[PDB]
Image 1 (cartoon, protein in one colour):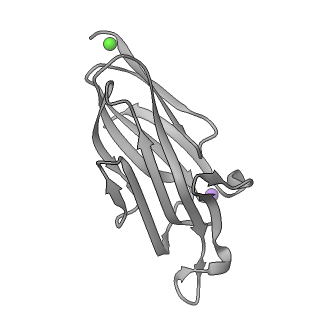
Image 2 (tube, helix red, strand yellow; image 1 turned 135 degrees about the horizontal axis):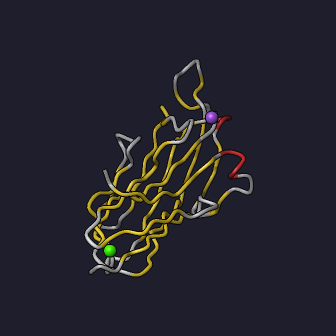
Length: 159
Ligand SMILES: [Ca+2]
Ligand code: NA
């Protein structure tokens, strides 16, 4: 089809949406940036939703999290590590690559269910209990979440 697909990327932890418009057959990266400021990520649990009528999921990863679990059936993932994952400056938390099959307008959403941040205890090289920050708990976001993170949702041609 010569008509296009507009993809809007949202997340509970993103104040703004991302958007792009693409040709049928194009490959598209939808990714979510997380910046943990002067802290690090300890734990995350998330689920991603998309419309299989319009997109085909080609890959789903946590590019910064080598020991993360991605469930391709449920389109979800999780990670937890006492050594932490350094998201200072902003890094990709989740990246989904799709092929555009259909046309119109569609939403891709990252639902962050759990998110805990922390800092290392220089004496141990593992997370300091007193540093831990409960950013999201069972889908409930902290009142001061955006004092502790920056985030962004991006939709771009795949390279
Ligand atoms: Ca077109
Ligand atoms: Na910074």
